[PDB]
Image 1 (cartoon, rainbow, N blue to C red):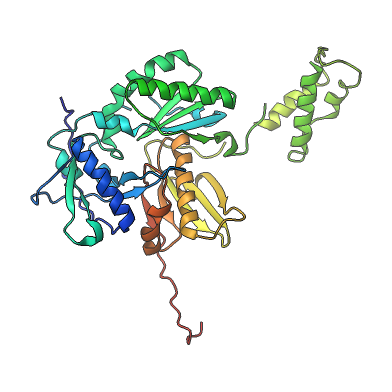
Image 2 (cartoon, helix red, strand yellow):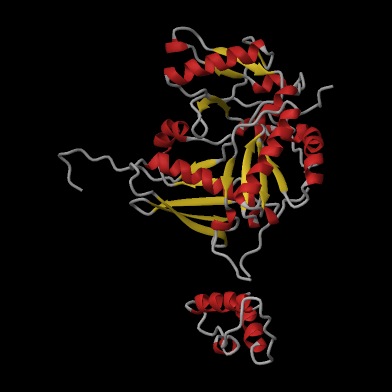
Length: 401
């Protein structure tokens, strides 16, 4: 029985023009869709259907095989709120040594979609070289990219993950849309095989996965701190921290390090050193509070060569996070391609940290972005974005600024 779903009250279905596509991407979309139809994942529809949603084709990682990407941003805004289902967002996830991202989207296609709602998923596939009108389809199954899919597939996913979660209590698995984020502190080799065990478990359920994507949230921000061998570790950490806090205490701890004492030797804790340790922990340890009910906003500025700066906030001037991205040496300069990668990363961070995608303000012209962005986009999701409003300067040769 299809889980009944409704649009938000007083809201109609999405109508969004389908953007023009390259012959190559079209030829891929046609072939992809022809097969989705044979499998009954989608069905042709008649002229009686007003609604439309935009579609494109991307390629993930090194894969030369095309993936279809539908833009549900409108539909998702207009869809009912599933929050009843949502399991508070894990804070520990961002702490983990390694976090891998799996695309579970294939799972959704085994679940039928409510017959009443299907009309709203309508999309148009342009023909080759626009020789004939485009063909319009809809979704008979939970589509990838629609916020309803994960909410409705929740119970089923929980069942699939249960055994592995029981078997690995120290591994955190968190889902956002079509992606499964698996964190852990395990040695990278151990972690990797844990992912592979997972992938083989999901495969037992018929759920197929593409090779994972490795993240190291450890390296996103600069971080707080934590036998004779151990006392050397501390002293080394304080000396390092000394270049930061001039008040860090050293000599008292150094006084205990004089000797031939072996690694095994256990040094006693003197009342002289403990003062330096308690005061050090004291210099170790505010910020701005994050409100789950509000929205995350991300502003991006271009710093002029390879450089881009960003801030993430809710109320202006109060920033939850600020950072910078820079173009690699030896990389061609393409501002859209670079900006596209920055947006995807900032989003990945927001997803991992607050479990939410920020609304973007992009330092670039609307036209440029909307033309190019799909070329460089590797993500299964798209955020909301807004372009700074200024007109670009148009100057002919014979004109003087």
